[PDB]
Amino acid sequence: DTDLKLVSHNVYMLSTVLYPNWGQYKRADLIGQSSYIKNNDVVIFNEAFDNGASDKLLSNVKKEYPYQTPVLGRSQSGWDKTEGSYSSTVAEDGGVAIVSKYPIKEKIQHVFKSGCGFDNDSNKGFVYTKIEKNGKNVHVIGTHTQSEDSRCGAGHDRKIRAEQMKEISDFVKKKNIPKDETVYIGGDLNVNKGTPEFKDMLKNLNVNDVLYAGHNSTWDPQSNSIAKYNYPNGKPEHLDYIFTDKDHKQPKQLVNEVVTEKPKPWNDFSDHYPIKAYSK
Amino acid sequence: DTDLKLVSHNVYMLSTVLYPNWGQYKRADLIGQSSYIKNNDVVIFNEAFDNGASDKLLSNVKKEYPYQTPVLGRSQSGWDKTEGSYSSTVAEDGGVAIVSKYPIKEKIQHVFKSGCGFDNDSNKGFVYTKIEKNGKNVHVIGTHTQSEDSRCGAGHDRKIRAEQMKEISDFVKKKNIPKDETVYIGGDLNVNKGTPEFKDMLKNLNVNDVLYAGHNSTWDPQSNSIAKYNYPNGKPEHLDYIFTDKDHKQPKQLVNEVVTEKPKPWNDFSDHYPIKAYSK
Ligand SMILES: [Cl-]
Image (cartoon, rainbow over all chains, first blue to last red; front, top):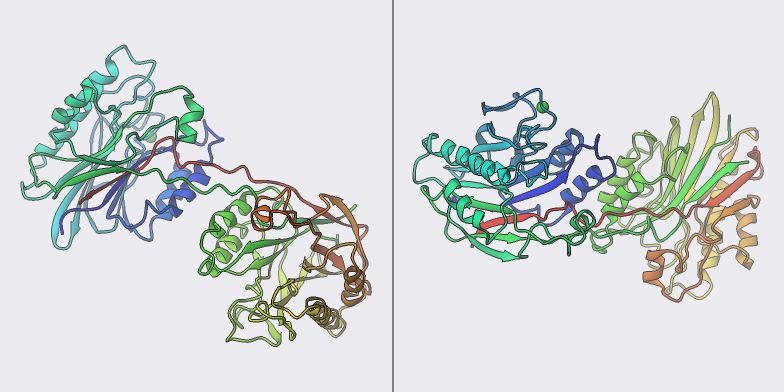
């Protein structure tokens, strides 16, 4: 009734201009065709940076999830409200967007005020949506927090992620949402499960941990072709989550299921080859 | 000036309803992206049966080849003229379509009158197009004749293929096309090269043999992943051709080149996996 079936998914669409050979396009189509993307109520996207592939993606899933938001921190247009340190003069956007099966009553973007090197030359932040499903109001916040970056002063990734999450949980309190409506928060939060920092994220976001299902890492270089190419001998991390603010209505038993769907490789175009014909 | 750069290609898109795990969709995208499909004047498609992937395909290539025909035998609409034993009560269409860089001044479909089992519960036949390039008229007939079928009475494959081709070469005589304009005929003709039947096809289609380049088979179980899956220990055939009616202008030196391009195919959606969230 009021509990949704969300999907978050960092989709690793880097600016096709600086990073040209990653089929950002080809993969946005692949996503549209996947099973996992079907039959949900709201989807949160992350690292959806590239304007083109951004569109390609949001477009594909427009049929089923008609109600969408801009991509966080791209422009001030199309948003009901724009708060925090939004900059026009920065390199990339927040790469966060929310699509939805049911009507979006309100959409608001928020650019984090704090930001560590390389990642702060962008409008990383969070997107808030009030959605109306079956007469009741529900709330979804998508975000993609500070990434672990080499540039960053040792320990800054965490100190800043903390500021950034406090920015979120603060936005929720001040938003005055009635205690009997659910508020979801989720996306690539860049904090590995079962670490010191995880305990902090729970407090800073003001959420409770949830129940997990399926795969036990979301960034897994070992079982995951693209992760593997980038960091061959790297340790898998569980970075993507969907929580619910603890001070508002809790869904019946909230689960996060990591889904490991992979596109079927086609190694040839057809069982036949093509004929070219010309006059030499 | 009047001679074209064609591509025919049987694309093995069976009805996604009876044959669902063949990425007919995923493959129609892959084709749009290939190299071989670029920089031609006319492309002929075959076994383009499924309505959905049919569209996906015809859509991808619309940019470069705007002028298209419907898929042979699907419906009577969109066709300037509809001759032969077209039926409405058959299972599948002819799966033949022609797209083109230059305008299509006339498009006509023809359903073969003869048909051998399994393959005859369908509107297999040929598509004719008059196309206008640089002021001159040129003519392209795509077709996909009777397939070698187990059901078929021993020897009927061939006897019907022959009727069907005579139906084409007859359509060409009675079409009153000017001897000084070229008439191309091509597609999976289901006739292996260097066999007895091959000599017949040349007479029945009223064409001359051409010069060959590149790979020497078009259906090759051994180098082609899909062929291999279906007929592991099967012998490679040359089945796809593009000839020109011998009683009309001949191109300067016609060549069929079998193109052995192979899609480099991505394996994961992102470096991250998707999170599904729900309340169980
Ligand atoms: Cl910007």
